[PDB]
Image 1 (tube, rainbow, N blue to C red):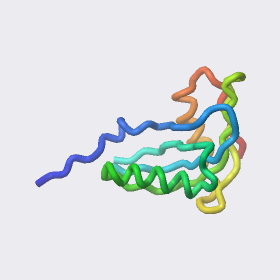
Image 2: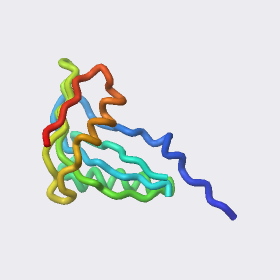
Image 3: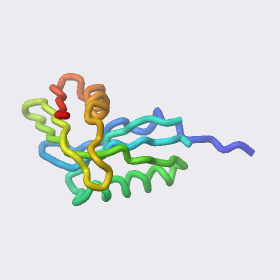
Length: 116
C-alpha cells in the first residue's frame, strides 16, 4: 500500500508563549516534505525539553524532525515587539533571521527583530 504523509501546511509555523523571555528552538520538520518551525515556551528548563516535546508530537503524526538551533525569544505584547537572540548549548544558535521570518508572518503588526 501507500502511506499518507502529514500535510506540513497543517503544522503551525510558530507556537510561542507571550509576555516574557523564554527558550526557543528552530526545528526542521520532514513529512517524511519539509519546513522550519519556531517553538518557544516558558515552561522549558532546557532547549532539549522543547525539542523532545515537539519531536515526540511530530513522531506521533509520522513526521521526523531535526533541531537547527535555539536561543531566546522576548515577547512583549504591550509594545508589540518580539526579539529573537542567543543560542542553545545543545543545538547551537539558530539562524534567528529564519525564525523571525516565521514570526513576522504570524505577527505582521509587531516589530520583529533579531541579533546576529
